[PDB]
Length: 475
Length: 48
DNA sequence: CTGAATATTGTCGGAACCAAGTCTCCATATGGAATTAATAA
DNA sequence: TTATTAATTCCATATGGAGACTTGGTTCCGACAATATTCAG
Image (spheres, rainbow over the protein chains, first blue to last red):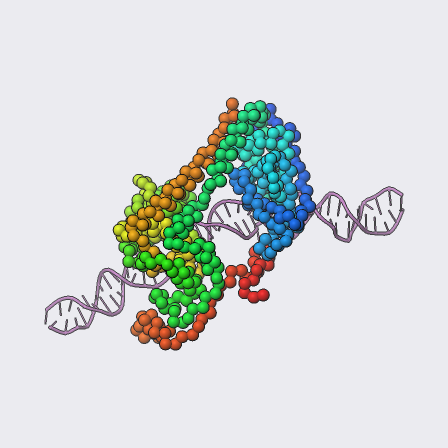
């Protein structure tokens, strides 16, 4: 760890005479002609607004605000106050609400390192109320300049005054009033304005345009799979909401082989019967399976010194292994080679939530190093003449595999529902001809590749939007 | 107790010969959402 | 008749913290292997 | 005339655990100022 050395006098920096390590990691003699909170901003005391009842107002907690300074408020109305959102209305009635005045900045008080600072823009409409967990400041200088100087720069001095105290690392208005902002950093940004606002505005509107067409990695798989097979997605989500199945005693042993009569199995049967009403290409998977080798999960330390190991978070709805190992072991089992990922392998997740169990992916990434797949991965070397593994993985990630594994995953603990080899061998999935399987794969490969390219341009723009600020400040 | 059988082939015909309806249903919300800081009301799918 | 001190009225400040989301090593059969084995020409 | 079991070892493997670690931020009690009070010199 760090080894510093400070003096007694340095305990006089704050009237709270704190002497914690985190606060004084930043404390040091200063030569820059620092500014203070008086010149830059002004803390605005919070007040409880008089909300009307007819108009549905919009509320936002800390969790609704994103890391990149976006708000996703919840539309609440006193007219429809049910028990699901009763807690929010309880907070509102208690008095944890305030309407930000236009142009202010709202810094979150809890956990500053997430950089959850939001700016109320001077333009636009439909103002949104916020939880008093934020802190209002009125920037005497240009609001956008202070906003960008607080998000990108000064992100470590704000994090150097947070108070943990047997729990949440939180801030206080006094902590902000204690900050020691520099002069050159702020005056360089303020003087070089009228272009450092135009460039950032253009880049932000480009980012907004890119986000305007973004789609999730699951809807794309759902869209094309719904395009084929002529599946009414609206009716499927309606039959899934039914909570009443009345089967008979005779229809318990049909294709059971182990006498399972739980409600989940009996609703699986109904859903699978509904899904295949018009599709006639279905054959059991157990025919086209050659092996079901599991993985190896030794005791692993995060960021250790040894062979890397994958995790359940590296399987995405796309169908490609993320190959982003985090955990590392140093233990051997005399059979290391059999538990190393190879190009073309088909891995299915074994053990997750009821909605994320059974996700499959093909490696499709040439990596020369050896990476262990945990025992929560089932590798499925199969017959490469009818299945076309990519198609199988993307079928499993689709609603055709997200509903079967949602109701066949055995387990007492619903948080780690697991699938066994028997479910894989007894799964009746639709197999179209090899030519027909290739067409879908091309579609939900090109569309998702375009989506990923969208996901890459936005990151590059958001990185240069702060590189510009850094180079402007330090100049 | 079973008699040197697989009990599946036997159980199929046993259930075929004698049959009775069975009732199954699922509740999603029970109405007593508890946390380490007390209870809280919720919709109750079981009874009203 | 100028109090300040107790009925309390609504607001800060913390918390042997704690829900939300979702990712895990390991004890325990187990059976198909091995083994012993008894079939029987 | 042997070599089939079927028991007794023994393996790496499949299965499952009234789980359990990670990350983020939430309620609620306790002060507490400021209501009020409050009787009195």
